[PDB]
Amino acid sequence: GAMAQTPIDLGVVNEDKLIEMLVRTGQIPADASDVDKRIALERYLEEKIRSGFKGDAQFGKKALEQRAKILKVIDKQKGPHKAR
């Protein structure tokens, strides 16, 4: 009854299996050493507060750090309405 599951260790032990699961879920890039592991670990446990854990992290170095805004083409058109 355990084919393929998320590592449910619930604590410190989970850090081993997190080497796969974090990167797998897209939480942290494939280029992630134990230097980078902290970023995804702190984030992981804290975001789990929405499902039942706690926070106390409030840190996760900007991995994506991408742009987010659209302009110029923000406008409506005016085609037909009523001929006859």
Image (cartoon, rainbow, N blue to C red):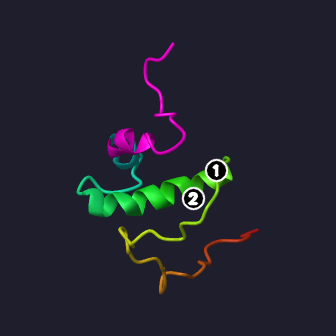
Give the overall secondary structure of the magenta segment: loop
In depth, the one of 78 and 74 nearer the eye is: 74
Residue 78 location (% of width, % of height): 62, 78
Q: Mark number for residue 46?
A: 2
Q: Which residue is mark 1?
A: 53
Q: Is residue 29 magenta?
A: no
Q: Looking at the image, do the residues carrying marks 1 and 2 touch, with CB atoms under 8 Å apart?
A: yes
Q: Is residue 11 above or below residue 66?
A: above
Amino acid carrying mark 1 in the image: Phe
Residue 27 location (% of width, % of height): 41, 54
Amino acid carrying mark 2 in the image: Glu
Is residue 51 shown left or right of residue 70? right
* Residue at the image position 34 percent from the left and 49 percent from the top: 23
Q: Mark number for residue 24?
A: none
Residue 42 location (% of width, % of height): 48, 60
Residues shaded magenta: 1-19
In depth, the one of 45 and 28 nearer the eye is: 45
Q: Label 2, secondary structure: give it.
A: helix
Mark 2: few/some/many CA within 10 Å (<14, 14-19, 20+) = some
Mark 1: few/some/many CA within 10 Å (<14, 14-19, 20+) = few
* Residue at the image position 59 percent from the left and 51 percent from the top: 48
Separation (CA) of disc 1 from disc 2: 7 Å
Point out the residue furthest to the front here: 12
